[PDB]
Image (spheres, coloured by chain):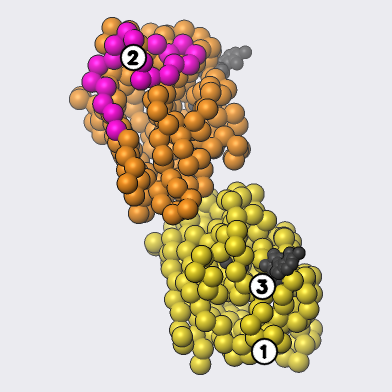
Chain colours: A orange, B yellow
Amino acid sequence: TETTSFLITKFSPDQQNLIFQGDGYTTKEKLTLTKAVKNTVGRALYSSPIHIWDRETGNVANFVTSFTFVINAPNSYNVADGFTFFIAPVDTKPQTGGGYLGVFNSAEYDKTTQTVAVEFDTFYNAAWDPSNRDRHIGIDVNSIKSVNTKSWKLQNGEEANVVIAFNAATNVLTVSLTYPNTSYTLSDVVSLKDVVPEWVRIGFSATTGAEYAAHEVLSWSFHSELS
Amino acid sequence: TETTSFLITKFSPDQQNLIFQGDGYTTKEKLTLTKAVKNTVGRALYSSPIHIWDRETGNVANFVTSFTFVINAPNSYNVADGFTFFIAPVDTKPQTGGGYLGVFNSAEYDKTTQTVAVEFDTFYNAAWDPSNRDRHIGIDVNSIKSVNTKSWKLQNGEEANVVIAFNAATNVLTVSLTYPVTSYTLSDVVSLKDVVPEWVRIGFSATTGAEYAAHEVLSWSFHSELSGT
Ligand SMILES: OC[C@H]1O[C@H](Oc2c[nH]c3ccc(Br)c(Cl)c23)[C@@H](O)[C@@H](O)[C@@H]1O
Ligand SMILES: OC[C@H]1O[C@H](Oc2c[nH]c3ccc(Br)c(Cl)c23)[C@@H](O)[C@@H](O)[C@@H]1O
Ligand SMILES: [Ca+2]
Ligand SMILES: [Ca+2]
Ligand SMILES: [Mn+2]
Ligand SMILES: [Mn+2]
């Protein structure tokens, strides 16, 4: 058995178990991935590599992460681009900004990205986003074009409680988002061992483009178990 | 409802609803995929594209195929490489030979291959095959390294009756082989709609490598039903 777990109830100014990229930084109880400014990207990774699957045994990890995030849009109707929770190679680095959310580079499947992300997408990108043009939760596998999405009403400035669980027996990745004032779930079968390397880093990403909003994380826990 | 169905109880020398690739051809009322010769490949596809899933609806077809095959190994202990029933893009062509069975090119997941195969694998390839080194039935998804396998004792020269069924309610692919030891069954979830295009061709592949055997099919039926709701 190999397990990794952590809990951050409130971020500190020197959150040394996080790796920051782009504009990500911790400040005043919060993890800020971006401020409400154009054309930016912020990411933060958990410091330790996580052992998500093993090939000798072929086993995959069960894991769960929960976190509370806030999107603060100065202009409530012009919100972009969103935020994600992601699983990527250990040396992951920010990818394209804007509608690509800092985690992918194309709406086509790219095996070299080796990334699974759960996106909370505030801006309709016509080339790939769901044609109903709603903001949406999505599950992304090596592409910005989600393999499954669920429409989602953003509550500007409200705390969103997210739980993301992966069941290694069924390859099922479940997402839930809850506001204090409304609940959304979304699941899909994800063959993690075919997507991400055996070791990964996990983290958050958020971006802005021509439209913008602040993206913040208030707390984060994670637990994986690999038999 | 969109359905594709066909039955061939015995192959004819001019089987025009099959597309042949490599060494495949029909003779003496059988489909021959390879003769007992080294380093070859032979495939046969049903002619018509088959509508296996639909994006607008998200629906996946239920389907069942059943066929009888024979492996005739001149050398009973040195058998290779095996045979498959496969689902692939409409323009599918033979892929790597030998232990790759003419359907895959790697033991790592390859999205672009877009192929599901059910393998009847007679030769232990150390780089990916089950480490007990048994001959084995396998379910292969974009890789020659099966997502799931079941040890299978080959009966040389004997007719093997195969049924492959896909339950679209559960995305469960089930394989059964029966020799009329005597029966083997293997199941796994296959997310077809993530792997193959909406339109597919189905067919058989067989290969030999440094070791060899004849791989033959004696009959084939298929039926898929894709719901429109
Ligand atoms: O922030 C939302 C969007 O901003 C940009 O797209 C544009 C939306 N309106 C525009 C107007 C002009 C120009 Br130039 C651009 Cl790139 C855009 C791009 O960065 C997109 O990737 C992003 O989704
Ligand atoms: O037909 C069975 C096998 O034949 C070849 O592997 C070998 C089996 N015995 C050998 C002996 C020598 C050499 Br060189 C090779 Cl490549 C082989 C290769 O073509 C394998 O891919 C295949 O599974
Ligand atoms: Ca978007
Ligand atoms: Ca083999
Ligand atoms: Mn999206
Ligand atoms: Mn095999």
Q: Which residues are magenta?
A: A5-25
Q: Dot 1 lies on which element?
A: loop
Amino acid type at circle 3 is Asp
Q: Is residue A85 visible?
A: yes
Question: What is the chain letter for disc 1?
Answer: B
Kind of residue at disc 1: Lys
| Above/below status of B18 relative to B181 | above
Q: Nearer the viewer, mark 2 or mark 1?
A: 2
- Mark 3 and 2 residues: CB-CB less than 8 Å, in contact? no
Report which residue position mark 2 lands on.
A15
What residue is shown at x 72% (from left), y 91% (from top)?
A: B29
The answer to whether residue B162 is magenta is no
Task: Decide if residue A157 is on the left or right side of residue B201.
Answer: left
Please determine if labels 1 and 3 lie on a single subunit.
yes
**What is the x, y in percent for residue A119?**
43, 30
Q: Position of residue A168 (x, y in %)?
A: 36, 50
Q: Is mark 3 within 8 Å of ligand 2?
A: yes
Residue drawn at (59%, 40%) of the image:
A111
Instruction: Report the Cα–Cα distance between label 1 and label 3.
Output: 24 Å
Label ID, residue B81: 3
- Identify the element where label 2 is drawn: loop
